[PDB]
Image (spheres, rainbow, N blue to C red):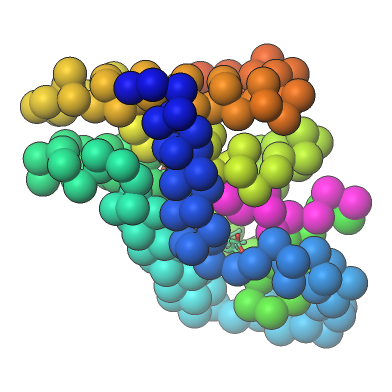
Amino acid sequence: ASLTEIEHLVQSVCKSYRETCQLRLEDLLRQRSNIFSREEVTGYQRKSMWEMWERCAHHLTEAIQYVVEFAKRLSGFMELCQNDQIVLLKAGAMEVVLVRMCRAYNADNRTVFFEGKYGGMELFRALGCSELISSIFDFSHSLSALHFSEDEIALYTALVLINAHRPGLQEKRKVEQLQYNLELAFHHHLCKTHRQSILAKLPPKGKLRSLCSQH
Ligand SMILES: C[C@H]1O[C@@H](O[C@H]2[C@@H](O)C[C@H](O[C@H]3[C@@H](O)C[C@H](O[C@H]4CC[C@@]5(C)[C@H](CC[C@@H]6[C@@H]5C[C@@H](O)[C@]5(C)[C@@H](C7=CC(=O)OC7)CC[C@]65O)C4)O[C@@H]3C)O[C@@H]2C)C[C@H](O)[C@@H]1O
């Protein structure tokens, strides 16, 4: 590929992200003022783990669907054999969900957008997995510190998915070729935007992988 083609890849990854990002960043930021009352919090805390599980599983499944749509629009992803498409989404979709969450997270008050309003980790109490929710909130907290642009998320999450080191891949060389082009697309766009500094500030490789493992 040439540099003009990599620019086309950047714009295309950024486009596919915008068309699949679930909620507009605009709306998410506007709603930061809209916070669950103490009574609303208590309403969530009173629900059984079973109701909370059902709701959360629904929102998660929905988010994963958007991730799958995003991957399907990535260049060459549809050209991969069905086995590798599945391998890559299985290992990487949840990781993408967790990176995308940071757009919906307000570090000023450690709250997250959930079912129309912002709420803290205590909203999820009935699930009885406070270590997990706190680790999910803390990861969003550290990502929010970097002020990820929409295009940085698009390109970074394309790379979370297109990773030739996933076990079980059958056409490893094809995935590699896609990965290298996306790596150069990312580096090149950071240089275009004077954002080279975020490279050293990214989650250490394995952090994201192990947070979704025990999940
Ligand atoms: C490990 C132990 O787990 C024990 O049960 C567990 C397991 O079954 C696992 C089970 O997973 C939950 C849990 O992970 C929490 C999880 O909670 C979900 C809802 C809350 C989330 C914080 C979270 C992460 C994505 C995040 C949502 C909130 C949404 O509004 C978003 C902000 C939304 C938006 C994005 C955007 O850009 O705009 C809006 C899309 C998704 C979103 O990014 C997923 O929902 C999942 C279903 O939690 C149970 C308690 C049993 C044993 O003790 C076992 O040994």
**Quarter where residue 159 is shown:** top left
The residue at 45%/54% (across/down) is 16
The residue at 78%/83% (across/down) is 40
Magenta stretch bounds: 98-108
The answer to whether residue 141 is visible is no
The residue at 73%/71% (across/down) is 27
In this view, 112 is above or below 199: below
* Residue 192: in magenta span: no
The answer to whether residue 87 is visible is yes
- Residue 214 % position (x, y): 43, 38
The quadrant in which the C terminus is found is top left
Most common secondary structure along the magenta stretch: helix
**Quarter where residue 109 is shown:** bottom right
Number of numbered discs visible in the structure rendering: 0
- Residue 99 % position (x, y): 57, 44
In the picture provided, is 159 more to the left or to the right than 186?
Answer: left
* Residue 101: in magenta span: yes
Q: Considering depth in this image, is 131 or 28 the residue closer to the camera? A: 28
- Residue 192 % position (x, y): 67, 26
In the picture provided, is 201 more to the left or to the right than 84?
Answer: right
In this view, 41 is above or below 206: below
The quadrant in which the N terminus is found is top left
